[PDB]
RNA sequence: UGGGAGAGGUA
């Protein structure tokens, strides 16, 4: 155990050992953007792949061409924090050497005429942060990965969508990456068809004739021949015995002297066996057998040259007579059946109205571009550019793989375009599906759906911008001359920036990141969406794709999804899931070999795991060898059954393999019903971080993994000792073995303090290490918002009781004690930003100033001399933070004085109060002000003071980090010189400037001293360079929006306590609203006088079946009992030996638990620190589907001297009497969700109204009224409340001359209205009149 | 061929195709 | 059969009494009281809590050959939970659609 | 002024 893990060891109850640890949780986004942005020699990904897909490009003449050489990315102009402050995107400039060579077409090949190349700036691409996010326009975004269908060919049939016959219609679909589609399909008349881009149908031989295949070659490709042999007016036929399958023999087959079948006798397999053991080949057939067949060969006459019979036509008596007199004594008809070799292609050729390649191309043109006269070159060019052109069609190397795998081919590579053999194989395979061999494809398989991620989507949008810029530069180099043109002036840098900024700003998958807690960030980054560009559509999707497929096991979580209309469409990645090189999801598995479950870990896709047989995770082992039973439970082909121990092929790598992260943080998940487990996994992301975070007593073990992998903590990069801990800076002196020989060995960890998140919560990092403590590589130094000692901590441990309390927990409601409120347990900080921007009106500019017309001195009591509020001012609702007055002339006038400005005169003076006020009911201090003035004007005194504060702060920060690095470098200098020579006192009495020039002759330590002296020189050089860069960066102005003079950004900080109305929740879907905050003398209490903190209703348990709530309550009671015993020993100050014995006795309690915490290897101060962290309860890891049982829970409760049934006697706090039945009391982890009644409470009497409708606005932000909808109108109509309904429709709404009358009538004490016509009805009359329709009211 | 079209630029390009280019 | 055994054992195990003899009466188990009063619960949910979870269905409307032989007190394994998620997500989509 | 889209969430 490490020296930071000995501080608080979570007692794991897990039984199965962790063979493979949980991987990096954010590997998907970071790996996708790294593949997009890195440089690759031949395996082209991203920018190099697009820059080779679009370059080089010549003219129409070939006089010149532009070549791509190499690309690089410059340093971003602003950092992450500076982009988040200034409100700009975090991007790096793209520079690429574009080589322009000039040919000489006047010469035969004048290749070298003029060669130009320079680093052309082609837009900026937004960089990804170290946590997986994109800072776009000052807001942090997350690009959600997409689940779309893979490119390739998919065979599927409708399930009888024509009940006139009940037939099923098999069909194919060749989906490319980019390019048109292709849909071969059947009809109820068994005639194949073709839909290109889902347009009107054409017969499916039009494509074959367009592929230069005549009717002869079509019939050879799609049929085999029953060859006939007519000699001297008796017909014989060359018979292979594998052609007579289950039909009544209308004719009798013969031999040389043998008779086999009789009249009216169906052919049997026994007779087929008879024929293949007698082995006759040539059988005389009667005349009537050929009458009914279809000839597969056109038969020209050799004498007259007249075509006596073509191919694909029905024969007859006169036709066979014509063949016999013409002399073709070997006629060839195709083999057909009625159950296994259908006459499909013959009927399609009969219904086909074209007979030539050119007429087929004309028909394809008339289907594609209707209402246009076709020609030869346009029809041929359109059909070639449909599928057989590299720049208008692409399967993109994953469609080729799925194409060859669906057609059972071998080579997984090839071209991206379609071909003759490809289309022929698709039609052949669809015919095979129709005949019976093979089955349709499962469209909800995860071998058919792939993961398209942020790097692939950014490569696609970069390619769109690239082909736009390519077209523009191609017409430029085709039109202009060649002597004065450069690549810099001929490449436009607008459309690539437009494409990538349109994507990264307002795509459907570029989402405003949820950062309530670290769990919300990690779940938003690990999200998979079925919607998006080229995916599904939300209202147009049904239960077929919103289901849990059996291939989702280990790849997609079944119990983390929203419960609204996005339920089967937004998904979450499983814990161990990865992607292929193609983008298909795969999950690890342990390989068994002769029963021995090895550590061979194989990542199998969904198509490979159906072939094998994979054992369950909950099957026991011995010595990591065989299975202890002989019939283990497995799953093959999607179904589950029992299998033998030598039959098994694979085994699951863990027990948390199926669930996602948030569904793995639920303890006792296997006792919760999946509905409430889904709701609890969703509600875990809505938890607000509190004032002091608290580790859960009943956890899982994924807490540390989430808290480190979320990137919200501050982990150590290298191991060493800690040199200085502030509340904003941790300095670590690195150990020598982890130190590079050229650096100073000093790590600086600046912490973020009170930064507003996306959901207006608090983000601040607090140091968890102390002064002088050692840390290792990967150690948590600073906690996050809702972390605690590197463990995820979303709520607080509340002593809970399950009983009804006077109806105060009636229907999911929660009764809360007063200690919860006094102890600030659910007190959350909500930082909130309000901006006041002084615009540029055309009547003059709006002035930010100290003087405000028509306010008292109770408004300017907190302002400064410049009009801005002071940093630290305890403002309340309605106070003025920054005063802004409009110029001479108002902007919108109130009707109380609008008539007084009309009849007396608008003064063209007396400016309007337009100040930034705190919203109503919102207290809080002011923690930061930021003024962004436009570049060019003199700013202000307060803005100048803020700028001097930033200047001296940046100088102090850079000089302090320079002094710290100088102290580290000088300590390394004195260490290496003490190791070299014996110079101790002569360097202490010498000043530190004379530490780099003295020494002795040249050795390894002298070279180290010289290179560290050069390190110090370049350190102070980069120090003064960065100081001057920061100085010019903070003195230069901010290029704001056009029309903006200056913006003042005020930052409030509200501290929110719980109150009745706040939604609280546990991890099992046990949500509800606080109904009352009870006094602690009124709360129920036990025999020791400890009152409970929260009273929950037990009626919410049985119909919802979330028993993990009750088991978490019991295990939390046992954990707090153990912590109470440790606290009693620490308050009695007993020993260290009895404490070591009791903590070891509590750690060794499980039945067959994996971890062995031995305290004999511990020191005494380590055991004392462990007990000081254990005195508030022993944290317990309960893995999902690997948890503690009732026997372990009851043994722990018997250790803690607690009742083993988990139910104690409670007394009423009011009457003093005892409750009759024993009540379940324990400790449950309760979260404060982000649905706060301060944010939901909103009332309005009269405010502002919409422009067109003259109805009130909508929202708490703009002070709007509640909608009285159609359903509420129906409710009032069903009551009969006609006057109430009429006053909802007119005087509380769009009756402009009636609502002012109603307001003055109410002020005059007269509760009577005078309603009139709704202005929205006048709007509707005007719109129907504008539609050319005379509607009018009729005066009787 | 006239008939099954509604795109007016397509109708313009169809009806302008009657005339021939000049030498 | 296991549901009938569960209902009998939950319904009448309170027998240890006096003053006429040891005699059977209606049980004061709180789960049974919440079920029998009609407060919150029913015998199907009590069967899922204490007896057997029952036969679940595939998403194509077909009942599986083996049922979930565990309950929520003992907990389900990973296969039984993944089997139950089909009907769970099907019902949760049907509520929105209806 | 206060509109329209897109995304997410609650009952």
Image: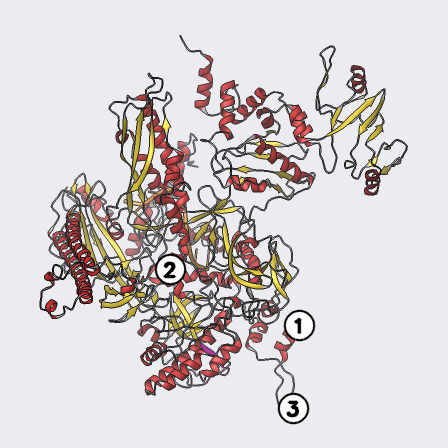
Q: Nearer the viewer, residue A950 or A602?
A: A602
Instruction: Say left or right for A467 vs A382.
Output: left
Q: Alpha-carbon neighbours of circle 1 within 10 Å: few (<14), some, or many (≥20)?
A: few
Q: Nearer the viewer, residue A850 or B19?
A: B19
Q: Alpha-carbon neighbours of circle 3 within 10 Å: few (<14), some, or many (≥20)?
A: few
**Residue A228: which quarter of the image?**
top right
Instruction: Identify the residue shown where x is 44% and y is 42%.
Output: A533
What is the C-alpha distance between the residues marked 3 and 1? 29 Å
Q: Alpha-carbon neighbours of circle 2 within 10 Å: few (<14), some, or many (≥20)?
A: some
What secondary structure do most residues of the magenta stretch adopt? loop
- Which residue position holds label 1? C4
What mark, if any, has residue A709 been given in the picture? 2
Find residue A503 and report its horizontal and vertical position in percent. 37, 42
Residue lying farthest bottom? C19
Instruction: Identify the residue shown where x is 36% and y is 34%.
Output: A466
- Which residue position holds label 3? C20
Find residue A149 and report its horizontal and vertical position in percent. 51, 44
Contact check, label 3 and label 1, Cβ < 8 Å = no
**Same chain letter for marks 2 and 3:** no
């Amino acid at each position: 155990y490490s020296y930071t893990e000995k501080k608080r060891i979570r007692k794991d109850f897990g039984k199965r050992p962790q063979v493979l640890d949980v991987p990096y949780l954010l590997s998907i986004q970071l790996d996708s953007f790294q593949k997009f942005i890195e440089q690759d020699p031949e395996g082209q990904y991203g920018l190099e792949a697009a820059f080779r897909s679009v370059f080089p490009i010549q003219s129409y003449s070939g006089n010149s061409e532009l070549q791509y050489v190499s690309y690089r990315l410059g340093e971003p102009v602003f950092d992450v924090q500076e982009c988040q402050i200034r409100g700009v995107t975090y991007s790096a400039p793209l520079r690429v050497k574009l080589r322009l060579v000039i040919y000489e077409r006047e010469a035969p090949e004048g290749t070298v005429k003029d060669i130009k190349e320079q680093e052309v700036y082609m837009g900026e691409i937004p960089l990804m942060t170290d946590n997986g996010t994109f800072v776009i326009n000052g807001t942090e975004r997350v690009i959600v990965s997409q689940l779309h269908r893979s490119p390739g060919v998919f065979f599927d049939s409708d399930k009888g969508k024509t009940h006139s016959s009940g037939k099923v219609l098999y069909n194919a679909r060749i989906i490319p990456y980019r390019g048109s589609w292709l849909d071969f399909e059947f009809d109820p008349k068994d005639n194949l068809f073709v839909r290109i881009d889902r347009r009107r149908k054409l017969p499916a031989t039009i494509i074959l004739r367009a592929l230069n295949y005549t009717t002869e070659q079509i019939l050879d490709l799609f049929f085999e021949k029953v060859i006939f042999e007519i000699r001297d007016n008796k017909l014989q036929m060359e018979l292979v015995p594998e052609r007579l399958r289950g039909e009544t023999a209308s004719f009798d087959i013969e031999a040389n002297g043998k008779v086999y079948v009789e009249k009216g006798r169906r052919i049997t397999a026994r007779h087929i066996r008879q024929l293949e053991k007698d082995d006759v080949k040539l059988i005389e057939v009667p005349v009537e057998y050929i009458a009914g067949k279809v000839v597969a060969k056109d038969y020209i006459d050799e004498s007259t040259g007249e075509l006596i019979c073509a191919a694909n036509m029905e024969l007859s008596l006169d036709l066979l007579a014509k063949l016999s007199q013409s002399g073709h004594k070997r006629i060839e008809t195709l083999f057909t059946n009625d159950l296994d070799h259908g006459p499909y292609i013959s009927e399609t050729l009969r219904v086909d109205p074209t007979n030539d390649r050119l007429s087929a191309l004309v028909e394809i043109y008339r289907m594609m571009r209707p209402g246009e006269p076709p020609t030869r070159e346009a029809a041929e060019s359109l059909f070639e550019n449909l599928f057989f052109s590299e720049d208008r069609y692409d399967l993109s190397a994953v469609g080729r793989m799925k194409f060859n795998r669906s057609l059972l081919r071998e080579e997984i590579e090839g071209s991206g375009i379609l071909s003759k053999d490809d289309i022929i194989d698709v039609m052949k395979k669809l015919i095979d599906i129709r005949n019976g061999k093979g089955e349709v494809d499962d469209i909800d398989h995860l071998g058919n759906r792939r993961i398209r991620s942020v790097g692939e989507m950014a490569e696609n949008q970069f390619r769109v911008g690239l082909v736009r810029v390519e077209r523009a530069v191609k017409e430029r180099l085709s039109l202009g001359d060649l002597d004065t043109l450069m690549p810099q002036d001929m490449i436009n840098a607008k459309p690539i920036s437009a494409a990538v900024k349109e994507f990264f700003g307002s795509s459907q998958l570029s989402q405003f990141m949820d950062q309530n807690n670290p769990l919300s960030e990690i779940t938003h980054k690990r999200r998979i969406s079925a919607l998006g560009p080229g995916g599904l559509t939300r209202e147009r999707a049904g239960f077929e794709v919103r289901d849990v497929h059996p291939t989702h096991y280990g790849r997609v979580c079944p119990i983390e999804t929203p419960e609204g209309p996005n339920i089967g469409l937004i998904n979450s990645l499983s814990v161990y899931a990865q992607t292929n090189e193609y983008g298909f999801l795969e999950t690890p598995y342990r390989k068994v070999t002769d029963g021995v479950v090895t550590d061979e870990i194989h990542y199998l896709s969904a198509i490979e795991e159906g072939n094998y047989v994979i054992a369950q995770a909950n099957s026991n082992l011995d010595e990591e060898g065989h299975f202890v039973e002989d019939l283990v439970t497995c799953r093959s082909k999607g179904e589950s059954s029992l299998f033998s121990r030598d039959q098994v092929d694979y085994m699951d790598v863990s027990t948390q393999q199926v669930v996602s992260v948030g569904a793995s943080l639920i303890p006792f998940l296997e006792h919760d019903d999946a509905n409430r487990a889904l709701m609890g996994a969703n509600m875990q992301r809505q938890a607000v971080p509190t004032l002091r975070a608290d580790k859960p007593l009943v956890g899982t073990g994924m807490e540390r993994a989430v808290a480190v992998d979320s990137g919200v903590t501050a982990v150590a990069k290298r191991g060493g000792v800690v040199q200085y801990v502030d509340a904003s800076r941790i300095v670590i002196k690195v150990n020598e073995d982890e130190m590079y020989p050229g650096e100073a060995g000093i790590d600086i960890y600046n912490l973020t303090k009170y930064t507003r998140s996306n959901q207006n919560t608090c983000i601040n990092q607090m140091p968890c290490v102390s002064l002088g403590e050692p840390v290792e590589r990967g150690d948590v130094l600073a906690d996050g918002p809702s972390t605690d000692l590197g463990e995820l901590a979303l709520g607080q441990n509340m002593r809970v009781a399950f009983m009804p309390w006077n109806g105060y927990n009636f229907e999911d409601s929660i009764l809360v004690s007063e200690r919860v409120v006094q102890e600030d347990r659910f007190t959350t900080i909500h930082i909130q930003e309000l901006a006041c921007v002084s615009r540029d009106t055309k009547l003059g500019p709006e002035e930010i100033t100290a003087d405000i017309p028509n306010v008292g001195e109770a408004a300017l009591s907190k302002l400064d001399e410049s009009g801005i509020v002071y940093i630290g001012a305890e403002v309340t609702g309605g106070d003025i933070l920054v005063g802004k007055v409009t110029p001479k002339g108002e902007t919108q006038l109130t009707p109380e004085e609008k008539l007084l400005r009309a009849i007396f005169g608008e003064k063209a003076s007396d400016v309007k109060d337009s100040s930034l006020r705190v919203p109503n009911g919102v207290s809080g201090t002011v923690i930061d002000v930021q003024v962004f003035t436009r570049d060019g004007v003199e700013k202000d005194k307060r803005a100048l003071e803020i700028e001097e504060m930033q200047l001296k702060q940046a100088k102090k920060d850079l000089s302090e980090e320079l002094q710290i690095l100088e102290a580290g470098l000088f300590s390394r200098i004195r260490a290496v010189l003490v190791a070299g020579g014996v110079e101790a006192e002569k360097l202490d009495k010498l000043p530190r400037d004379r530490w780099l020039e003295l020494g002795l002759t040249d050795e390894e330590k002298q070279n180290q001293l010289e290179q560290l002296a050069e390190q110090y020189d370049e350190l102070k050089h980069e120090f003064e360079k960065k100081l001057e860069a920061k100085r010019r960066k903070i003195t230069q102005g901010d290029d704001l929006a056009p029309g903006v003079l200056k913006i003042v950004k005020v930052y409030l900080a509200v501290k929110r306590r719980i109150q009745p109305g706040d939604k609280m929740a546990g991890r099992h879907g046990n949500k509800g609203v606080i109904s009352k905050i009870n006094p602690i003398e009124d709360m129920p209490y036990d025999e020791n006088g400890t009152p409970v903190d929260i009273v929950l209703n037990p009626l919410g348990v049985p119909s919802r079946m979330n028993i993990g709530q009750i088991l978490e309550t019991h295990l939390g009671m046992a954990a707090k009992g153990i912590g109470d015993k440790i606290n009693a020993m620490l308050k009695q100050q007993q020993e260290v030996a009895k404490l070591r014995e009791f903590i070891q006795r509590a750690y060794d309690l499980g039945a067959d638990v994996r971890q062995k915490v031995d305290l004999s290897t511990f020191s005494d101060e380590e055991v004392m620190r462990l007990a000081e962290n254990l005195r508030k309860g022993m944290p317990i890891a309960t893995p999902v589907f690997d948890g503690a049982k009732e026997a372990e829970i009851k043994e722990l409760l018997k250790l803690g001297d607690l009742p083993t049934s988990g139910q104690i006697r409670l007394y009423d706090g009011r009457t003093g009497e005892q409750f009759e039945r024993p009540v379940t009391v324990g400790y449950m982890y309760m979260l404060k969700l982000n649905h706060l009644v301060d944010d939901k409470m909103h009332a309005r009497s009269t405010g502002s109204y919409s422009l067109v409708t003259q109805q009130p606005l909508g929202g708490k932000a703009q002070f709007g009224g509640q909608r009285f909808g159609e359903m509420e109108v129906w409710a009032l109509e069903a009551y009969g409340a006609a006057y109430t309904l009429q006053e909802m429709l007119t005087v509380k709404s769009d009756d402009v001359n009636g609502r002012t009358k109603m307001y003055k009538n109410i002020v005059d004490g007269n509760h009577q209205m005078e309603p009139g016509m709704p202005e929205s009805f006048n709007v509707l009359l005007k719109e129907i009149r504008s539609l050319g329709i005379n509607i009018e009211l009729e005066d009787e | 061929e006239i008939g099954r079209t509604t795109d007016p630029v397509r109708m313009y390009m169809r009806e302008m195709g009657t005339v021939e280019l000049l030498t | 059969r296991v549901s009938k055994a569960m209902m009998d054992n939950l319904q009448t195990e309170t027998v240890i009494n006096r003053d006429g003899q040891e005699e059977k009466q209606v049980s004061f188990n709180s789960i049974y009281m919440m079920a029998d009063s009609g407060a919150r619960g029913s015998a199907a949910q009590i069967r899922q809590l204490a007896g057997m979870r029952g036969l679940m269905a595939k998403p194509d409307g077909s009942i599986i050959e083996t049922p979930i032989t565990a309950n929520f007190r003992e907990g389900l394994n990973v296969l039984q939970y993944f089997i139950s998620t089909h009907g769970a997500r099907k019902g949760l989509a049907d509520t929105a659609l209806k």
